[PDB]
Structures are given as C-alpha cells and as structure tokens.
Length: 274
Ligand SMILES: *C(=O)/C=C/c1ccccc1
Ligand SMILES: [Ca+2]
Image (tube, rainbow, N blue to C red; front, side):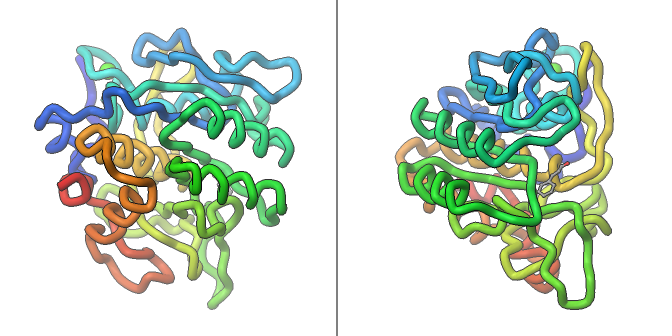
C-alpha cells in the first residue's frame, strides 16, 4: 500500500494530478546530497556529481533522497506519492554525505542544470553568505527560463532580524518557508523581507536511503513542494515563462499573515495551474 503525505492534498496537488497533469515531460534537477537511485519508488533519469569521490546516484546522507521523493515519488502501490510523479528526475550532487558543499560545487551544479535544459531547479540548502558567482549563476538560469526554488532557511525568528540565507535571498530565486499540517508556520522557518511562499515543511514523510521512508523537518522539505508545483503548472501550460509560473504561485497563494513571516502565503497549485 501507498501512502499520501499530508503535503500533497494540503497544497491541492492531488486535484491537479486527478486532472491528469503530473509533470510529464518536465525536467527537474535536485541540487542535493545525491539520490539513492535504486530506490523502488524513484526514477532518476540522469544527473551529475561535483563532489569528489561520490557518484551522483548514491546518497550517503538521506537528505537528497527525501527531497527527491517529495517532488516525484512514483505514483504506484507502494511507498509514497510525489507532487509531480511523472517528472523527469535528475540528481545533481553538490553536497557531500555530511550535507555540506562548496560554493564552486554548487555554482557548477547550477550551471550544469542550466546547460542541460532543466526546467526547474530545487536547492534545499543555504548559507549565511552568498557569492557573486552563485548570484550570477541563478540570475542567468532564471533569465534562461529555469524556475529556481530554494529553502528559505531553518533559522527561525529574532526580533526584526532577517534570517533568510543564500541562494534563497536572491531575486532570481523563490525563497520557501515551512508550515505544518495545520498550516501554521513552523517555529524553525526563516523570516525576512525576501520570504516568498510557504509549503509543508514539518513532519514530512518521503523516500529515504535504502528502500525506506522517513519523516523530516525543515524548509528543505518545503522547497520540493514548490518545485513540484512549478512542474505541475508547466505540464498543464508548457507555454509559460519562468516568471509567469513564478507569479502564478505567489499570486494565488492562500494568505496566512504578515509577509515577513509567511510571504504571500501557502501555495495552492490548483489555483496556480488554472
Ligand atoms: C535543509 O534541511 C536545509 C536547508 C537550508 C537551506 C538554506 C539555508 C540553510 C539550510
Ligand atoms: Ca509510490
């Protein structure tokens, strides 16, 4: 039997899938710690690794496999179901097994995705500081027509202080925050002017290293929900430009409160893919 994580219906992804739109033909690149490509509930089509000593189709951490599951866990009779289960999945390793990567490695991953025609780029990662090379890479990917989504950060609140990290803080990237199954913002969600939209980030059940499934907390989990949404909006209207897909997501988001804490609100893909 196959489980449906609360995040799927909450963002109304189930309604879009039922219409027949599941992201078929859309290329999504997950810039993470890799993916356990042999997982029975995943179908990695390709990818690349910029981490020394590790191939792209192995995940020694678990993080990348969990993020990859939220976006496209296969729709079958086992495991879980992803936001866009028919998406073309590419694993781009930019982080090591301990979950950390160098700027050059990330920038290399962003460029690889831009040159290989990826439609969406999910980056469930972030640093306190940015870099001109990284900023330039995302601006260019977005300008080339790629949707760039990034985890806002698990830094929480601090009296006015903006806690959004990079690359989420760039204009060319969608900064995603986290809400729980009750739709209340999770305590660990970063807050700041750059916050754009919210998505399920707490108690998220997804695929996990060595043919299993686990629950994780973080804006790392929220991010793949938006990348999966973008893929869904694109499989229904392959004619839209990145900024158009982007605007559809925030324009139709369900308002939750002050943009400093929730951006434009919780995403509603049934409204966005209209
Ligand atoms: C996810 O677990 C970590 C995501 C992330 C993104 C940006 C800044 C810090 C951490
Ligand atoms: Ca499944």
